[PDB]
Amino acid sequence: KASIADENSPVKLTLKSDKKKDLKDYVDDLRTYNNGYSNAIEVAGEDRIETAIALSQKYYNSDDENAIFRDSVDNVVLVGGNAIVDGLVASPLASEKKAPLLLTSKDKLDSSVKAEIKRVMNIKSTTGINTSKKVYLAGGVNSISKEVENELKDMGLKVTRLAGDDRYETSLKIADEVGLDDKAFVVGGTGLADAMSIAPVASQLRNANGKMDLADGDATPIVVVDGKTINDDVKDFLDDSQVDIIGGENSVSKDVENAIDDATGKSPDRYSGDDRQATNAKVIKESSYYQDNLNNDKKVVNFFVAKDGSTKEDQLVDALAAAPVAANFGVTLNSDGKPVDKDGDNDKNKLVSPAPIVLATDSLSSDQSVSISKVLDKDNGENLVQVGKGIATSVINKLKDLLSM
Amino acid sequence: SKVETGDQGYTVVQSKYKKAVEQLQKGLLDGSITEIKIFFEGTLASTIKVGAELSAEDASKLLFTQVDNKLDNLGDGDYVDFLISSGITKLRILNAKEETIDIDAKTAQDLAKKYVFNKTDLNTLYRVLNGDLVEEVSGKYQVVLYPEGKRVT
């Protein structure tokens, strides 16, 4: 008694058990797997270009649930395919600019990408292309050539290039576009895997107090410096900012840390481990990164998975495009900035729950397991996303056990 | 007063057609059912009021006459609903398949990879099964479940 069913419900199920306890073990198993087959997703493609495209089509300008935007976008951040050196910091850029970060080839603007640009911006054959839509090109001429820049300009789009004479100068030009409203992040460029572990945190639209504000909030920029001392420009950029330096001594030397000490007058916090995975673990278990950024009274329920730089550091570019997605996750926004399900206590900032990107290709470390177990809520996992191909099933199996999905 | 999905009431499969109507008929005669309103595909079929110059013995025969042909030729997505009044009660007859899983023996991970269940239904069911409906039928503790659909592959 007490519930009538859908007209088209295929089968009527009855669970017969001698004891109620054995039934609880079967309903819980059913509840976990049912919510562990529909909530665990996979976004990937054969090449890194279509992977970023599929990551865009699902979370940007898509009618499905668990997307970032359900309507047209006005900006797009474009980065080269093999442009991990110059464009790593574009994740907070795509975040504040409320733009999908897309990967293009160096010399030829892919037809797949150009279609995605027009699609995500609601550009169609009956609408004229004006300077109301911008395409931010992050990187130098080896990231996005002049051939691609002039094509995007020929259509009529406003093309803003964020480039410099060096990778370190390029990142400063990018971090200048990202509003430093008094915290920052520093990475060395020797370890790019450690920098990708901090991309989801830096891309969060956060408030002054450290909580999350998707309206009138800003994301925290990242800077790449040599690890030596602090040059004339980065010291000017860092005025009274709380630097959260990322990486070991081999990435950024203690001299570079001491120079920041003398520059900004604040003590820089240091997150580092012997391995690129251990650095990821310490970033996830940091309270002020994920747990304390939540306006709601829950813990970390959303999680992401991506490859690392063990096989090839180039493969880590998959986690770069997923950072703007993992930062603003758990809420879907329309043109006016209101939450939806198909249309529409339930405030946006109270509903946002960002997701840390876990770096693992072959196996998941014990430190990463302990760290991920610390941040999980009592009610356990609610969304897991696997970005890219080549991730071992061993890792995904361990994740589903940690998150109970 | 209207019948619609996700409401408090009874659900019968076409396999249990013969039994459901018997209980409605025997309830109608033994002064236990006063009024019945039949709904074919969410549209009103006819109203049986024992007090509308009718009788219980006539209403019992009338009820079976209307729905014997409809319910014997049910199609996927076709349903017959009743608003049973005892003085209140809601019923829906549909043509799904019935499958019983005796756990004292299909595991749950094979069940989930095939059917899509509502989380809010399983959430409440788990809670009321351990602490804060489930029936005891002939030494067993049975629980009925209605999936929303089949799982994508």
Image (cartoon, coloured by chain):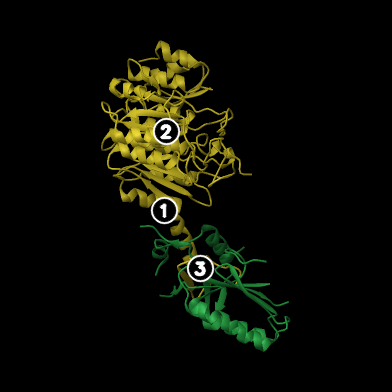
Chain colours: A yellow, B green
- Answer with left or right where residue A385 lies relative to residue A214: left
CA separation in Å, label 1 and label 2: 50 Å
User: Residue B90, image x and y in percent?
Assistant: 62, 72
Query: Which label was assigned to residue A401?
Result: 1
Rounded to the nearest angstrom, the CA distance separating label 2 from label 3 is 50 Å
Are the numbered discs 1 and 2 placed on the same chain, yes or no? yes
Residue type at numbered disc 3: Leu
The amino acid type, in three-letter code, at marker 1 is Asp
Checking the image for residue A259, the label placed there is: none
Q: Are marks 3 and 1 on the same chain?
A: no
Q: Residues within 10 Å of mark 2 (few under 14, many from 20)?
A: few
Residue on which the image places disc 3: B145
Q: Residue at 53% of width from left, 51% of height from top?
A: A378
Please check whether the numbered discs 2 and 3 fall on a single chain: no
Mark 2 vs mark 3: in front? 2
Q: CA distance from mark 3 to mark 1?
A: 25 Å
Residue B85: x and y in percent read: 69, 75
Q: Disc 1: which chain?
A: A
Against B143, residue A89 (above or below) is above
Q: Residue A79 in the image: state x and y as whole percent.
A: 35, 28
* Residue A352 position (above or below residue B23): above
Q: Is residue A376 left or right of residue B9?
A: left
Residue A279 seen in the current view: no
Q: Secondary structure at mark 3?
A: strand
| Nearer-the-camera pick, A19 or A204 | A204
Indicate which label's residue lies in the foreground, 1 or 2.
Answer: 2
Residue at 72% x, 80% y: name it. B52
**Which of the image's four quarters has the N terminus of chain A?**
bottom right
Task: Check disc 1 and report its element: helix, strand or loop.
Answer: helix
- Residue at mark 2: A126
Q: Chain of mark 2?
A: A
Residue A380 placement (x, y as % from top left): 50, 51
